[PDB]
Image (cartoon, coloured by chain):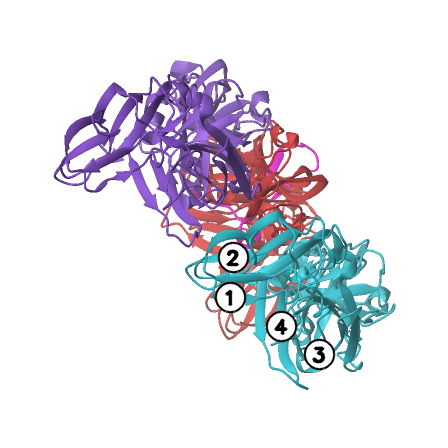
Chain colours: A cyan, B red, C purple
Amino acid sequence: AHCIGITDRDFIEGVHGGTWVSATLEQDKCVTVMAPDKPSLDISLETVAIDGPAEARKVCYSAVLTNVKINDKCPSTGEAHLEEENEGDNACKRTYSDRGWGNGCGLFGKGSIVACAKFTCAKSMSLFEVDQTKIQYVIRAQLHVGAKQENWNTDIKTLKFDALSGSQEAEFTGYGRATLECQVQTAVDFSNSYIAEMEKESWIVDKQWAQDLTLPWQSGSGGVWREMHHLVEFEPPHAATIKVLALGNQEGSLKTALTGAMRVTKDTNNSKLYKLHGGHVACRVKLSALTLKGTSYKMCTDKMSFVKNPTDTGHGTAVMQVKVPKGAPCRIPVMVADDLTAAVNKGILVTVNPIASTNDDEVLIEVNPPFGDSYIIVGRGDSRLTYQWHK
Amino acid sequence: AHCIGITDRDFIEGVHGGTWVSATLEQDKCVTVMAPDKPSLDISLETVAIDGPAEARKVCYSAVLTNVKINDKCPSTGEAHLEEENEGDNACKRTYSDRGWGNGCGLFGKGSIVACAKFTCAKSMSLFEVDQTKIQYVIRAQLHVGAKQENWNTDIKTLKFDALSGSQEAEFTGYGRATLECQVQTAVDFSNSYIAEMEKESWIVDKQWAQDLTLPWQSGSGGVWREMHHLVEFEPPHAATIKVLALGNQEGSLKTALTGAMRVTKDTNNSKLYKLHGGHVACRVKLSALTLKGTSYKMCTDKMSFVKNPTDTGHGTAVMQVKVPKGAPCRIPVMVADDLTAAVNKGILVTVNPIASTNDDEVLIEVNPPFGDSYIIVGRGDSRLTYQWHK
Amino acid sequence: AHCIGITDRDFIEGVHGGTWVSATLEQDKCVTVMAPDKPSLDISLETVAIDGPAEARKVCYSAVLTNVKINDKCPSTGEAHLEEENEGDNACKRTYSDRGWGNGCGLFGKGSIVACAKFTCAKSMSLFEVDQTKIQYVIRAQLHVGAKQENWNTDIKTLKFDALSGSQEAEFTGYGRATLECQVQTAVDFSNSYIAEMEKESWIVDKQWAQDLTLPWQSGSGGVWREMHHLVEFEPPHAATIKVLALGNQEGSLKTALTGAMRVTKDTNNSKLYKLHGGHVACRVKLSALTLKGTSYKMCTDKMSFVKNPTDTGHGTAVMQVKVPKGAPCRIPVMVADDLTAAVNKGILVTVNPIASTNDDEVLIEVNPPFGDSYIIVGRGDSRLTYQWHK
């Protein structure tokens, strides 16, 4: 019952017959869906992911200007030039200096200076495109067979999806089968956004934001960086010198903007998987094909005992564990009542027909008792167990 | 006259006699000072040097965070512990986590969790206290003797104003002496500030700002880093685990905050001299002890020549060089006239009395011609040089 | 019949259908359960306990500051540090002192000073976290066999329970057996608390209160104390000196807060056991398997005598002890009548069928006389003991 452990649990109540029940899931939340006689079904998300998204940009946030040269010409001697100015790895600026006799010229007009510097990205973001059609989904499903928690880790059923895959069927030994539609494409519309990756961290952010970044960037595998001035200061030109300086590591400013984004976690082993949080889904549940097991076994009579008392899940339910020490595969009766007379059950039972699978067996039960005080009763008979519960 | 070569130049005229004159000097700029019968003096502020600061703080802008450890305890089994928390260099944080029957406990309350990791400073900024007793103001002074531009740097006098040398005497060969008072005590407000130094760039910064930085720091002599929570962030705990992530390198953000501070350049030679950019100082000039070297001389009447023609420095003054190949102890007649008949002189000479003193002497002359059309006339008789001018 | 010894006694009565009777047992009170046709039961809550709580915090109420070191620096020579400041068992404070030539400092102004002292707890309050699942309790049961007060502790049955021993059976020789089924406690009053222990005094305290105490604390594994500044007082600096003094022993203030808490007591022999006062336990009693020992026996006729004359219990009942010196394997006829025509036993007998069993047996009888005047009567004609009793 994986749904016991997730704080955001929702309960959905259904109807009999050949019918579907609607549900919606979020990556941190779980639904228990219940229906008049079907064993109740737990459903949660497990991942939303893209596999091998395609490179779309690199954006540079630290650069080294490895060498620099200047050319300068007197005010009447025309425009200055440097052969580096036409070579793609060099950031170059043209501007006019204050020439004169003090600086080695015959005339006092404005002179011409060019400054060029060899660029090199030290560290850069990789921006990856997400094809909204290629996203992958995984759903967890369970029925309350009444298994102990030491068993959940194997009983849990994993339903894998992609945005193109159809409704899928789950098989539970004995209880039969279910089918879920999950129309994921109506939930997530992450087109017009893309994955921004940085060393050991990643985000998803809007493309129009990223294109508008005032940082130098590269259009693909190799080739020149395209807006180099966004990382290079050229000082106001002196007589024949322009000090050029790199603007320093912009990792911290870039992270500051990303703080609002939905996070992305790179898979530790299937290296090219990128798990994408926040994305929800809508699903509809074919409850009709489930069945209870063992409806026709005998009801218990043995002197049962608690393995753990009822405890408040915070979902409003009480979860409890019981054992039949020396019985056949008997049905374990349970009810909630206003008084020891117990003339009727007055509560809702999540586990619908708990059965001892073996002669020594231990079983889990969960109940949703009404408001106020009520007596939880298990083992209707002379040798009743009870716990005086309160909301 | 080095101020022919500085693009921001002001003119000041003393009432009479060189009695007492005032100026404000700013690092980019120069003042030319005139008086009715005394040689003109060029004054400018060369540098404002601060000598031998002492360290106050280092502020770390990029921490590498290592050897993370976590400990967590079941939701009603007391509170967490790590030995690493005894050590001042681990940035440990303590909180609570959702727990439940599927996550290692009998209860559904909140389990205490604590996580520690070692904060190592990869790069840090040095803040220095500035000794306001050790500020040196350097003024350059030279006369308009008529020296050619190759010689200006050997004619210039350099005067240094520490807090004690409040009045200084400029001496010139033959032209007498001039006294400068520079009011260092009212020039800057250093006491409430620190030198901030990053690698090969430095700033002078307000002390309140430097201390109110939300960024982790260490005492000048070393020891412990005091405010590590400003760079170490802890993501909200999953059931059994908490991930700690270092915030990025803040260099670009720190420089962005510094976009308003006055830059300071460290000396290549004296490893503890710091030269402030953009300072100013109020100064006063006593001209009364200057003399004009050659008022006793004869007039020229020989075949003079232009080594450099009058050229238009943007100050609106015409600068020329005349060579006097014959009569040596002689004065050059210069006038600017509205017509070649030379009926009146319409230009102030800045070189107040251009004397030759060898049979080959080359004398720079600067004239302030009137608005409209005029003739710069140098010489007498038939050997005159006459040059047309226009504002 | 130990209900006699407990002042806060309630009577509860059965109905001839033999239904379970439910009763509320509270730590100072006692209950006599009377059946219509079967012997009456003393039932009373003896203890409620936790066996070995979980150690959660020690909080310090008396402290000593065993070693003190101070460091001071001049106003323009940086900021002071100490090796102790890196070392976790030192409490530390940083501030500034007014320096000047009067204390060896060359510049007048505020100078940084820092002081550190070794914290050491002399007495700490232990706080143990209570866990409802570990609560234990004990009920005492005793039928009104008629035994001497001197024989009660030999004859009472002590019934132990825990959260999982669902029901217990009490066996009374000859009279048969009864079974109790119980809530481990109804006492939700203990929720969200700690057991607080000082030397030989203990209390139950709200978790919020205990954690918000302005006193330094540590986790039970032996950490280092987390808020030492609550007990170190730092004198304002004077030259190079700070005096640090320990704020005094807080035992009385902490006790003054604790006066409202429910008391907790520690066992003398099994020191992990804390007896938690003030609880409510609810139980059901199965009366059906009780029986009356001697209903077939002869009815007394030899002269009885009073060992203790009838006396007022304060519960409205009267108690006597009677001696049967001959013929003793025989029923003692006791009745309360309106007058010596002895028409009917207008009273209710709590000792439902007093039998003597040995040739000099002495038997206690408890009667509930009617309102108004009455005669207590025991025996048969010409041999009746009688005693006037008025409400």
Asked if one can make out residue A236 in the rendered structure from this viewpoint, the answer is: no
Judged from the image, the secondary structure of the residue bearing numbered disc 1 is loop
Disc assigned to residue A376: 2
Bounds of the magenta segment: B258-282
Q: Which mark sits nearer the N-terminus, 3 or 1?
A: 3
Q: Gap between marks 1 and 4, in whole Å?
A: 17 Å
Residue B376, by quadrant, is bottom right
Are the residues flagged by discs 3 and 2 in contact, CB closer than 8 Å? no
Q: Which mark sits nearer the N-terminus, 1 or 2?
A: 1
Q: Which residue is mark 1?
A: A347
* Residue type pointed to by label 4: Val
Judged from the image, the secondary structure of the residue bearing numbered disc 3 is helix
Judged from the image, the secondary structure of the residue bearing numbered disc 4 is strand
Q: Gap between marks 3 and 2, in whole Å?
A: 41 Å
Q: Nearer the viewer, residue B74 or A229?
A: B74
Disc assigned to residue A33: 4
Relative placement, left or right, of A107 versus C190 is: right
The percent position of residue A378, horizontal first and vertical second, equals 57, 56
